[PDB]
Image: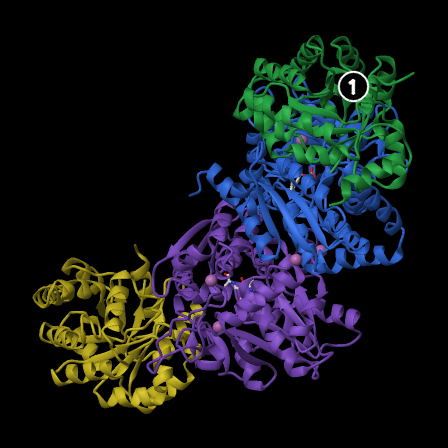
Chain colours: A blue, B purple, C yellow, D green
Amino acid sequence: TSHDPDSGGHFGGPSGWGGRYVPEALMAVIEEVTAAYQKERVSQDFLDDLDRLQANYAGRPSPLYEATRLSQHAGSARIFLKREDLNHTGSHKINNVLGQALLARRMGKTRVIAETGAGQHGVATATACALLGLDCVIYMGGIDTARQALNVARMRLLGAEVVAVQTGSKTLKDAINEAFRDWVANADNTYYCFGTAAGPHPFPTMVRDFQRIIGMEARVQIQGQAGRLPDAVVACVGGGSNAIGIFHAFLDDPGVRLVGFEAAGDGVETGRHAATFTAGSPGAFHGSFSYLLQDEDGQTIESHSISAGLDYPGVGPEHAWLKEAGRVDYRPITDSEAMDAFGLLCRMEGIIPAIESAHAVAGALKLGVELGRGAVIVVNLSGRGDKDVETAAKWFGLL
Amino acid sequence: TSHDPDSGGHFGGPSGWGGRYVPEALMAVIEEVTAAYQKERVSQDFLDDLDRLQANYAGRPSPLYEATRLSQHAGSARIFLKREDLNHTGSHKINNVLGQALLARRMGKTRVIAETGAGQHGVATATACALLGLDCVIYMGGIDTARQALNVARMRLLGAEVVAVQTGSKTLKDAINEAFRDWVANADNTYYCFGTAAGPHPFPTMVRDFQRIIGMEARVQIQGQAGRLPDAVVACVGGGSNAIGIFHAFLDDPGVRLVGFEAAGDGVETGRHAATFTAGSPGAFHGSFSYLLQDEDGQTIESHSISAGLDYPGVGPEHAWLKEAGRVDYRPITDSEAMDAFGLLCRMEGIIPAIESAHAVAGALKLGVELGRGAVIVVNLSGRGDKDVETAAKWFGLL
Amino acid sequence: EASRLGPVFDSCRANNRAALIGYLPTGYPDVPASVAAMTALVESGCDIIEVGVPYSDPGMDGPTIARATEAALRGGVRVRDTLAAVEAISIAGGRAVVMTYWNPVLRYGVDAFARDLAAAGGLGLITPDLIPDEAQQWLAASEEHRLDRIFLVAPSSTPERLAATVEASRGFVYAASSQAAPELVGRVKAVSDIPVGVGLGVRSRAQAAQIAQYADGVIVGSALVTALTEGLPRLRALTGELAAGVRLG
Amino acid sequence: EASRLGPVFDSCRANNRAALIGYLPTGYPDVPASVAAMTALVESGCDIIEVGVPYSDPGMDGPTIARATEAALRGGVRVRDTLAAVEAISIAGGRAVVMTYWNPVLRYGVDAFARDLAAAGGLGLITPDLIPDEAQQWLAASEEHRLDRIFLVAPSSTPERLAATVEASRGFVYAASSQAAPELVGRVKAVSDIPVGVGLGVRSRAQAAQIAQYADGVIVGSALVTALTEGLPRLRALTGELAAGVRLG
Ligand SMILES: C=C(NCc1c(COP(=O)(O)O)cnc(C)c1O)C(=O)O
Ligand SMILES: C=C(NCc1c(COP(=O)(O)O)cnc(C)c1O)C(=O)O
Ligand SMILES: [Cs+]
Ligand SMILES: [Cs+]
Ligand SMILES: [Cs+]
Ligand SMILES: [Cs+]
Ligand SMILES: [Cs+]
């Protein structure tokens, strides 16, 4: 495509987003995965297997739903929810996992590892490994094991091993560090199922390719229901996989505004946020040159969010490129704003969203007030809120 | 119309199964719901409204997945799972609830009440009332509030009042008793969204008509994926909604065996079970003449199951009729059989079923042994197991 | 022919009073003490006794009666114990009807239960969860065994159902439930001469007197259970006050 | 013409022995103590000192180095402290290179860091998370400010990538790890005469001497950090033992 990187993984040529900022010790396996992806992405048997599982196992397509009770809270705009929350396992993560897990098996890898923050990527990875009969090990920050415990129990019921990570912030960044350490040691038998649109090439592109289905379905569905392309398509941004997945099909539609909403925690001026574009700067982190929260020597600054899924100081390189080009705008959403939107969606539409997805809904409400009556806004509803019901009930005093 | 009861709600003759064993104080509102449903079931605009929410809000059709990795435990039969676990809210309950909540709005009712055991009907009702702007009060047995607490928290986030019932067995039957009490006192403004294929007419027929979609879709899907009608279609049986839903489309396929699986708890010989057809007898209970667990004097015997959803000593009258007629067999499945199947499905296919639903899976495995290699068995996978994760994790020594 | 309860109401009307109709559940606080309480009601001037059959899932009883029926079932009360209560009431010179949910009657056998109740001197059956629509077997047992049949009407009953419910009743019509109670009684009086009992959470002389202006029978249940829980003397005193209340002068 | 560390490896090759290459991280247990420890390494016989830049997310470091760098960071260590340590090392007669993850170099500015490293007397940069594929800016800065560029090879390195990494390296090549260390040094010798340094969690005289039999340098890090934690006199003693080891082979 016109939006793809070069063979080294670089977007936008000489600004140099992406690439491979990893040790030589990881290159044999990174090259192996890259080549297996190039071979299998054009193999009808692989595409057929992936398609069959998306339909019959995962339940695609997800519907697009006009949330008419949100309209009066969104400047009378028309909010359409792309319901990735109804997928098997309850988020978009399953899209990327089905692709990568099929690929692990094609390569003859006998063990799969992954990191998880919210536990959705963990549960999805564990799900696909049960299906295909692969050993699975999930690395998860110790603070995330505690606040997303429903998902730890799901993972273990699915036959996955969970390793609690107690280093650094004990959140997603630290789970990723541990999983990279595991892959280095176990490269010849282990596939690393990377959960977001970040990391070294091929992961940003590959993850986006497996998530593209969201935006392709959404583009068809909105034309069918609304009679035209949207005024805006929006999504929350952690490392960037659900957002890039929904955005991609609209990249070449010049009237479609694209907006990513990132976690601002206690607020961007408080130093307890994960507002990577709002407050970070370019640097190399977790295998890519992208944006990150870093101090003046380039030490990683620890992120904070009420959402485990957006609590990541980095962001994928294709978003960095899209930001630089002016194609996508990125805007901060606080814990409070997200939670108000969470409760609103519960009461108005009977949908309990993921706290991650609630950030996108909150931003959509604000964007509705800007664009005004009749504007059509597609929102990626990336996941459901089972995992967050304890937290949300505690937030609203429902105990 | 062919399998329908008479205008008094009786299956099998003017004094057979079903009817209205209710107080006169409920007859005005029961007649009002009957007239409203008779009118709306033949309105294309009503069925359009329902179909539109089924597609865009609930994400129908649910897929049919061939669970090939169960085959060796099922005598090398082919188990196909009808994936109601992927519905919005996580069970078949939403199908019935959408119909009835649409009906309550058509009637001008401002308040909805419901009973719930597993909390899946309670969550679904709360969900529909949020979506349609109706006040919601849910009655749930205090033992069930404790073992399905994830669903209590959900209902409350959705804006519903949850009332814990301390009478009798503090389980589903006792929640139903309380709901009927509420209804007689609040009939002017209140619709009772009845959760299973039981109760006085019109509920057994109406609930079943709103669940028919499951079997309609499955009959098309299994012909498409297997090339023929199945050798059997099976389901778990609480009051009977999911089973009648999937069975109905196959009733006039004389080569298709229909098997219902009821909760046998510690075992049918222990007196701690809910095996209504195996150990019960005909009687009048909760508005219908049907089977129930009852002693020599006609007092209800309290049910027990590890499954909150199957823990009910009665069953719907259409199943009583289908039993009496020889069209469906009803068979006991114990807690242990159910939990073995629950675990097998998790490990083998990466699907965490509801414990209710795992009774059906256990039964299909046994049926598979009986029918043998190549037999095609459709299994209603009525719901997912998120509500049961803590119970299942404990059962399997995972915390 | 004349209903079994006809003479009691005929007689009450001749003495310018309502019939006092008293409910107690069999087996509360145990089988013998309940029989003693029901006898006491006869001795203290109840014209008719409603012998309640405790039921596991009593959807229409208020909490006082529900707690009492629960205690009775914990004590091992049986349906045959209600037939014994009827026998003892008949022996003491009283007039008993039974009030029951329908399933215990189905389990016993409708014909069998009507026969055995009639044999024990029972005069009728009050059926709070049986509507005439489902009463075919019961209507045939009722005519065969000369037992009255008391169906309920409610303020919400449609014109059509009230007329059919009155027509199917013998003995009295129970007007279960504020002007609702007199309005409901007046709707039964517009279509029929059958006596109408009124239940209204009555607990004092004053309230029984209020009801006796318009109704042929005053029904008291909750307050008798509450009185019995305190003690048999308290039951006697209350029944006495209610007996005075039903007489108008 | 020749690399900066070239005359060091020549002097070892003429004394019939391998170079002792010693790693310490800047700022552990604090900045002055770390410099006193690095100076002590020069005096105790280390031919090259690797000055580590502590990094917040050090993917490749084992537990001993990881924890020392975490403590150095809690104590406020800055990147400029590394350049101060290099200058102290060079003034003491030592030969310093810097080991750093790449982001700290990007943030400083690659050219500016090369310039400032060279002005401090630095001889080179070891880049454990920079492959040559991403090394354009660094190759340019390395040629201009006259710094060696030590890349890493691994047992898993394909033949194509091994050749490319060796070709891109000036000074030495870091062979990071069964019979796997000698096999990797062998594959580097087959395509290049460039010195090879071997790091293998060396703790002892015996282990250092084993490695000196096939490698041009013996890299010790973990063990030096473990020694400093006990005390400065333990570092001197250990480093003395390792100095004797590399002269054995
Ligand atoms: C980090 C993880 N999840 C992130 C997540 C996100 C953010 O990740 P993206 O890669 O930015 O889509 C959004 N929505 C849901 C429902 C999520 O679970 C995880 O499940 O491991
Ligand atoms: C009684 C309730 N649930 C029953 C249930 C059942 C049994 O109820 P049926 O009405 O027989 O379908 C099966 N599967 C699931 C997932 C269920 O939740 C309830 O949630 O209120
Ligand atoms: Cs597995
Ligand atoms: Cs971020
Ligand atoms: Cs779907
Ligand atoms: Cs049952
Ligand atoms: Cs156990």
| Mark 1 burial class by Cα count in 10 Å: few <14, some 14-19, many 20+ | many
Element on which disc 1 rests: strand
Residue A369 visible at all: no
- State the residue in front, B260 or C8: B260
- State the residue in front, A235 or B375: B375
- State the residue in front, B51 or B342: B342
In x, y percent, where is residue C150?
31, 76
Position of A345 compared to B226: left or right?
left
Identify the subunit bearing mark 1. D
Q: How many tags in the picture? A: 1
Position of C167 compared to D60: left or right?
left
Q: Amino acid at mark 1?
A: Gly
Q: Which residue is mark 1?
A: D124
- Ligand 4 positioned in quadrant: top right
Quadrant where the image shows the C terminus of chain A: top left
- Residue at the image position 38 percent from the left and 88 percent from the top: C140
The answer to whether mark 1 is within 8 Å of ligand 4 is no
Q: Give the quadrant of residue C106.
A: bottom left
Position of B337 compared to D53: left or right?
left
Q: Give the quadrant of residue A55.
A: bottom right
Q: Give the quadrant of residue B300.
A: bottom left
- State the residue in front, A255 or B41: A255
In x, y percent, where is residue B167?
34, 62
Q: Vertical placement of A288 versus B220: above or below?
A: above
